[PDB]
Image 1: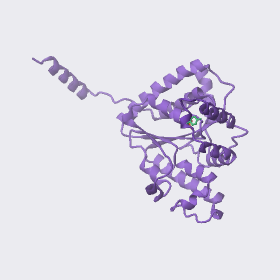
Image 2: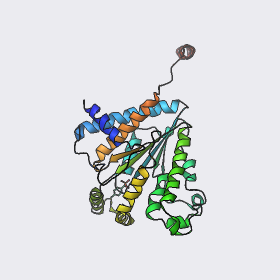
Image 3: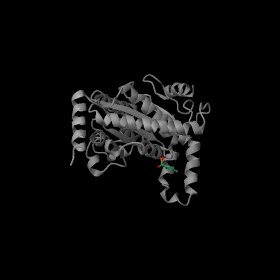
Image 4: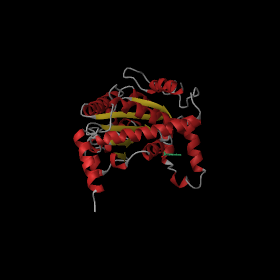
Length: 300
Ligand SMILES: Cc1ccc([C@H](O)P(=O)(O)O)cc1
């Protein structure tokens, strides 16, 4: 069956704890062996959205678990659109998107994790981090001079930023995700992997669209110029912060419809392990319902 092939491919996208990461050689940004048509996919995507809505409903009705979903990617990989599409099928009462832009003055007066801890999802809720605490081992690692401006970093000279500084930050991130995992939070992390070539194409496509080129950030080019620096940061990060408890998935991003299918797919598959069920109606409650129905019928 097609889905059976998909479940098999999906597992190759999970980053294993001991796994070493080369984003250049491995992790195709576009899956050629695509096992279903773009049509099939948009229909399996619809099912994934409906199922996720069902899961979210059952999650909200129970008071047990929260769900944290992290999205990281290079500009133009499809992150905002994946978030928007995940959302279309969710109830806004039980889901919350936080887009972590550049930190505020207050947030800079706290450790780099503080503002993400503040924004964690409550029991029964889904939290989506569009950008996340991982920015602090990515953009900060490509631009290590930012750490000098961060009062809590304890970094005075760029000389002291080395692999051991990042190792300690991975440890801090891992202890943080482990703690919340041990206290009811399901953590799922997606890196949307777009090719340097496809980013180029999408950048140019936007520049040439009058309806949308007002949105183009030419500063995105400065980060594109640091492509190799970012791949290294992502590689070292994926190799050191994917656990079985809080796994990373590397999603091919060059085909948006397929990116969305996979992420919807993985979220459903992972949250189905919770074996969530709608609340059942006891005999006492069934009696109360029939009493209420009787009164409504017995109205003058
Ligand atoms: C060219 C271009 C398209 C879409 C976007 C979105 O903001 P994302 O795919 O980075 O979330 C950014 C740049």
